Image (cartoon, coloured by chain):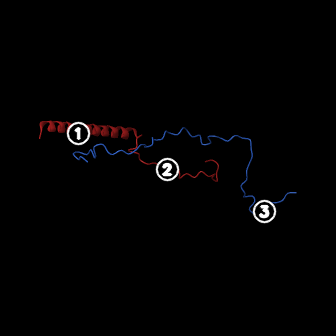
Chain colours: A red, B blue
Amino acid sequence: DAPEKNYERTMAILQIESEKAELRLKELEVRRLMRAKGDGPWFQYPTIDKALIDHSPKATPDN
Amino acid sequence: GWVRPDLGELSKVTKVKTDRPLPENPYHSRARPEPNPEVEGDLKPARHGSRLFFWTM
């Protein structure tokens, strides 16, 4: 093969792997911050839904 | 001149017209916490595939 072909093939390979590595580091930091703060869509442990609440007037007023 | 109620009449549910304002917060609830943001946007394909060790897809 031509030296130019190997040169530009290597540059394309290096760009792809650098992008993947930076994305992996971003994923790790995102996971840590999401677990610590809890506000993202991940690590959202479910709680009790509020459609199971009876809102009718009950038989005793003090409730 | 008082007529007794019939059967099933004193259990009727009525409407009451009064002058008191409606209590806005009878339960004394505090301010509710801010909800989580909702996921939005079109689903793009995954960047460079799996990104798991050496797998290129």
- The quadrant where residue B22 appears: top right
Location of residue A22 with respect to B8 vertically, above or below? above
Q: Tell which circle, 1 or 2, labels the residue nearer the N-terminal end.
A: 1
Q: Nearer the viewer, residue B25 or A30?
A: A30
Location of residue A46 with respect to A27 vertically, above or below? below
Location of residue A4 with respect to A54 vertically, above or below? above
**Chain that bears disc 3:** B
Q: What is the total number of numbered labels drawn onto the structure image?
A: 3
Three-letter amino acid code at the position of disc 2: Asp
User: Residue B13 in the image: x percent, y percent?
Assistant: 71, 55
User: Residue A56 in the image: x percent, y percent?
Assistant: 62, 52
Pointer 1 residue: A17
Q: Secondary structure at mark 1?
A: helix
**Chain that bears disc 1:** A
Pointer 3 residue: B6
Answer yes or no: are tags 3 and 1 on the same subunit.
Answer: no
User: Residue B12 in the image: x percent, y percent?
Assistant: 72, 57
**Chain that bears disc 2:** A
> Mark 1 touching mark 2, by CB under 8 A?
no
Q: Nearer the viewer, residue A38 or A23?
A: A23
Pointer 2 residue: A49
